[PDB]
């Protein structure tokens, strides 16, 4: 079905994969002025998939994508019904459903004043400042940047790992419609699961929404010291392979909670010990489907993060409907001595989470509500799965199966991932930005 890679905002389909990234949130002050600026800004800065997959030699110093909130489209006079059920009322209005603690959200997210967001991906912060200025210059006061969240890859060997220390970005759906390599174990879905209007999208979209996509953005603050402290105070005693020490048991616990070792080695393949080499191998680190641990939790818990967000075999076989693309990035400094040596967070660090799907309710929202937060999911298992330890928000946050030996044992885990704000955005096709929004 050959997708128009030159017209699709790159981050939706390929992911910026740049070291630094900045999210510039803004509200529209003067619509007319804004659309006019848009007409000159897009062709000059909005980077497409085609540009991201082309050789470095011709890529910008920084990538820029742009998304709008419902109130943003409203402010710009674009009143078409995009067809998604959550997008219209905003995420904060949906936060309770996600199981969020509203007291934790902070402005300017605690409402719908945010009209859209500019995603700037570059390798150096100074380039980030350069393009940031270019934005508030091309647009001047026709808009007002209300907040900017910036993130960067963690140092050295940690690059690519989120702040709890786990390698992130391993498993991603592969969509048909473009020449691309498929890793063994990688889901292959119709372009409609991610791009609105395309094949597989069950929603009813206006024609201009073609090749667009909804972004679920979550500003997460992570309590790292607390996380470690907790795994030590709960280190798993042993497993098939033998008795585990303190560290060993703690490391094993963390891995049991995620479904992967901090190295990326999926526990359904390295069930009793880490396999660094396997983790670093994209041709092997994702070739599993729990088909060998369906009715028992020896190889992998029923409620491990990755298994809850992508149950794979736990639901019969392949299913397109619930896959989504992720393009998140860590933020904040590393954990100090005074921090870990106290088990109490003393600095702001976390994840700037970005998830793309044609239907919010079938991706992020589904993974969150229907799976992660559902104690009875995966369905019909010998032992109750429980609440996903990492992002599940149903209380009591009780998850079972962590200890492979005495599986029935349950653990009520403290929430280490804290929602500070979020929003639902729509990223139109590059052409739509000018033919419809700026029109
Ligand atoms: C502080 C926040 C979070 C951290 C540390 C974290 C992320 C992790 C890690 C470290 C992996 C392993 C890599 C892989 O299989 O790429 C992964 C997987 C995944 N996570 Fe998260 N995550 C967070 C939040 C969320 C939220 C809020 C959702 C959805 C409601 C989610 C969804 C997914 C998906 C869909 C996958 C891949 C499953 C698969 O295909 O095997 N994550 N995540």
Image (cartoon, grey):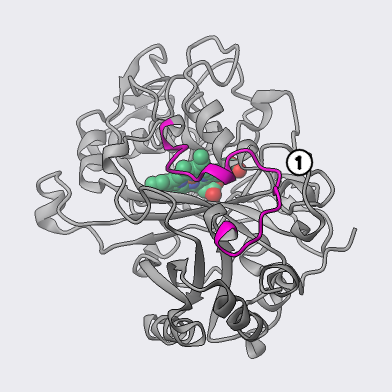
Q: Nearer the viewer, residue 167 or 429?
A: 429
Whether ligand 1 has any atom under 8 Å from the Cβ at mark 1 is answered as: no
Q: Residue at x 26, y 64 (%)?
A: 333
Q: Relative to 296, is 59 on the left or the right?
A: right
The answer to whether any part of residue 233 appears in the image is yes
Find residue 306 and report its horizontal and vertical position in percent: 52, 38
Residue at image mark 1: 203
Count of all numbered marks drawn on residues in the image: 1
- Seen from the viewer's position, the closer of residues 148 and 208 is 208
Q: In the displayed image of the protein, which residue is found farthest to the bottom? A: 57
Image quadrant in which the N terminus is located = bottom right
In terms of image quadrants, where is residue 160?
bottom left
Q: Percent position (x, y) of residue 188?
A: 76, 47
Residue 102 on image: x %, y %: 32, 37
Q: Is residue 85 magenta?
A: yes
State whether residue 100 is above or below residue 179: above
Q: Nearer the viewer, residue 26 or 193?
A: 26
**Mark 1: secondary structure:** loop
From the viewer's perspective, tell me whether residue 240 is left or right of residue 246. Answer: right
Name the residue rendered at 39%, 36% in the picture. Answer: 390
Label 1 neighbourhood size at 10 Å, few (<14), some (14-19), many (20+)?
some
Give the residues in magenta.
Answer: 74-96
> Is 352 included in the stretch rendered in magenta?
no
Residue 261 makes an appearance in the image: no
Magenta region's main secondary structure? loop
Residue under the image location 56 percent in, 41 percent down = 364
């Amino acid at each position: 079905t050959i997708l128009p890679l030159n017209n699709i905002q790159g981050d939706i389909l390929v992911g910026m994969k740049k070291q630094k990234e900045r999210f510039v949130f803004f509200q529209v002050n003067d619509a007319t002025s804004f659309k006019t600026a848009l007409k000159t800004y897009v062709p000059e800065r909005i980077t497409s998939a085609a540009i991201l997959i082309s050789d470095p030699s011709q890529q910008p110093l920084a990538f820029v994508n742009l998304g709008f909130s419902n109130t943003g489209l409203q402010a710009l006079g674009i009143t078409d019904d995009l067809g998604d059920a959550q997008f219209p009322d905003g995420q904060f209005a949906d936060a309770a459903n996600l199981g969020d603690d509203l007291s934790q959200w902070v402005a300017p997210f605690t409402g719908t004043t945010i009209h859209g967001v500019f995603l700037i991906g570059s390798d150096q912060d100074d380039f980030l400042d350069q393009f940031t200025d270019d934005i508030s210059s091309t647009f001047g006061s026709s808009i007002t940047q209300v907040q900017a969240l910036s993130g960067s890859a963690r140092p050295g060997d940690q690059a690519g790992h989120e702040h709890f220390g786990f390698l992130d970005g391993i498993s991603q759906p592969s969509v048909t419609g473009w020449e691309t390599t498929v890793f063994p174990g990688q889901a292959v879905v119709p372009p409609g699961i991610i791009l609105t209007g395309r094949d597989g999208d069950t929603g009813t979209r206006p024609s201009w929404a073609l090749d667009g996509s909804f972004m679920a953005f979550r500003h997460f603050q992570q309590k790292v010291p607390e996380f470690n402290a907790y795994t030590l105070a709960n280190a798993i005693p042993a497993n098939s392979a033998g008795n585990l020490t303190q560290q060993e048991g703690a490391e094993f616990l963390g891995a049991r909670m995620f479904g992967r070792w901090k190295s990326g080695a999926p526990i359904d393949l390295a069930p009793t010990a880490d396999d660094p080499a396997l983790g670093a191998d994209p041709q092997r680190n994702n070739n599993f489907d729990y088909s060998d641990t369906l009715t028992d939790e020896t190889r992998c818990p029923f409620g491990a993060h990755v298994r809850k967000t992508n149950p794979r075999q736990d639901l019969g076989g392949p299913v397109d409907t619930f896959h989504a693309m992720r393009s998140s990035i860590p933020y904040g400094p590393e954990t100090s001595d005074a921090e870990l040596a106290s088990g109490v967070t003393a600095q702001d660090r976390g994840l700037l989470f970005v998830e793309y799907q044609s239907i919010i309710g079938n991706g992020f929202r589904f993974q969150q509500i229907n799976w992660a937060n559902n104690a009875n999911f995966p369905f019909s298992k010998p032992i109750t799965p429980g609440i996903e330890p990492i992002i599940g928000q149903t209380t009591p946050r009780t998850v079972g199966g962590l200890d492979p030996l005495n599986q029935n044992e349950t653990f009520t885990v403290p929430l280490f991932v804290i929602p500070k704000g979020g929003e639902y955005f729509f990223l139109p096709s590059i052409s739509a930005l000018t033919a419809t929004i700026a029109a």
